[PDB]
Length: 122
Length: 123
Image (cartoon, rainbow over all chains, first blue to last red):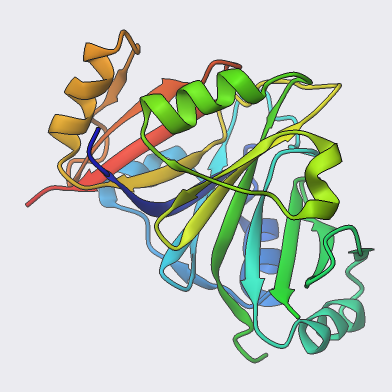
């Protein structure tokens, strides 16, 4: 078979109804992603989209939300140790991980309890 | 604040213990992604990694696996039309989505019940 898949366009992360202020304050303010406008048709669904490099993260509203604690997206970060201190400074709780040896990584939870990984190569 | 975040490096998709054969059959054979060897130190954890463009998908083993039927990763596809009919040819069930009119897209479930989305911009 031919090679159709070109990469990850975006990841969708779930959140409850009314999540927007908190989503904006964490993804936008705190970790510093740029919010982007949703397509006109999809606005009526609630939620927020944010840009990270050539990819996006779509925070989507769910009727019966449960956070994703295991499966999760991993974002590549420049200057990870500087970024991490910027998070710690803002009261974000971080969890370091040394299991993968040529990579620096840590985990955080978004305001809704969803697992996020940040990594950079050593 | 400076702009530290560069992109999505990978997505971790959960699966049960013993999933490797079924994961390779679907992610590798069916959808056609290239299997990537895991770091030596991580072998014992089970699971498999597949390449997609400058990104990866990591299938990670979970004893307490719960499939992600709603929140999911979305993969960009060239010639999605033709990709979709290649999946149907192989007996894969596809669920089209027409809500976003600038984009063609559809969902499938992997063998463990996780939702995956495929999309392409319209020309």
